[PDB]
Amino acid sequence: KETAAAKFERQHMDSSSSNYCNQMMKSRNLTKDRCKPVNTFVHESLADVQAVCSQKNVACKNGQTNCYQSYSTMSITDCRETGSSKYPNCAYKTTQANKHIIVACEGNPYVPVHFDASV
Ligand SMILES: [Cl-]
Ligand SMILES: [N]
Ligand SMILES: [N]
Ligand SMILES: [N]
Ligand SMILES: [Pt+2]
Ligand SMILES: [Pt+2]
Ligand SMILES: [Pt+2]
Ligand SMILES: [Pt+2]
Ligand SMILES: [Pt+2]
Ligand SMILES: [Pt+2]
């Protein structure tokens, strides 16, 4: 019964080390049945990420036009499973950057529902 907006917050928001991704991928239920291979966390306020839905309108990867690019760079952590990672012992490399995010927005209130990319 999780909404698309709630799922985006669970997978992609960290509004709060080398082991960050190992710990975060676990606590967000992204290693439950399989190791989710790639995931990005946004290290910004929920308000600042929701505001992206009023910024630069762009096409999404899938061809819809409800995508938005952040005008500002944001603090993000990229998590990517190692070559040698095997479930249920899921292993991630943690990479920090300052990049624009692209999100899909839907619904009322009009908030992020899908992490399209970082640029
Ligand atoms: Cl969707
Ligand atoms: N930027
Ligand atoms: N971060
Ligand atoms: N997403
Ligand atoms: Pt951070
Ligand atoms: Pt952080
Ligand atoms: Pt930029
Ligand atoms: Pt989606
Ligand atoms: Pt996602
Ligand atoms: Pt997707």
Image (cartoon, rainbow, N blue to C red):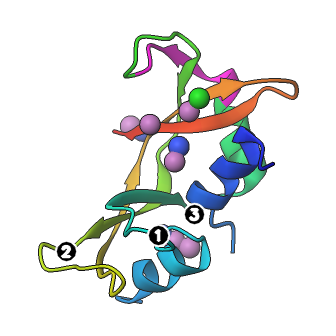
* Residue designated by label 2: 82
Q: Quadrant of the C terminus?
A: top left
The reply to whether the C-beta atoms of the residues labelled 3 and 2 are less than 8 Å apart is: no
Q: Residues within 10 Å of mark 1 (few under 14, many from 20)?
A: few
Q: Residue furthest right?
A: 108
Identify the residue shown where x is 39% and y is 38%: 117
* Residue at mark 1 to residue at mark 3: CA–CA distance: 26 Å
* Residue at mark 1 to residue at mark 2: CA–CA distance: 17 Å
Q: 36 left or right of 11?
A: left
| Span highlighted in magenta in the image | 53-60
| In front of the other: 69 or 26 | 26
* Residue at mark 3 to residue at mark 2: CA–CA distance: 22 Å
* Residue designated by label 3: 43
Q: Which callout, 3 or 2, points at the residue further toward the start of the chain? A: 3
* Residue designated by label 1: 33
Identify the residue shown where x is 75% and y is 50%: 6
Secondary structure state at the residue bearing disc 1: loop
Question: Where does residue 33 sit, x and y in percent of width and height?
Answer: 46, 69
Q: Residue furthest left?
A: 83
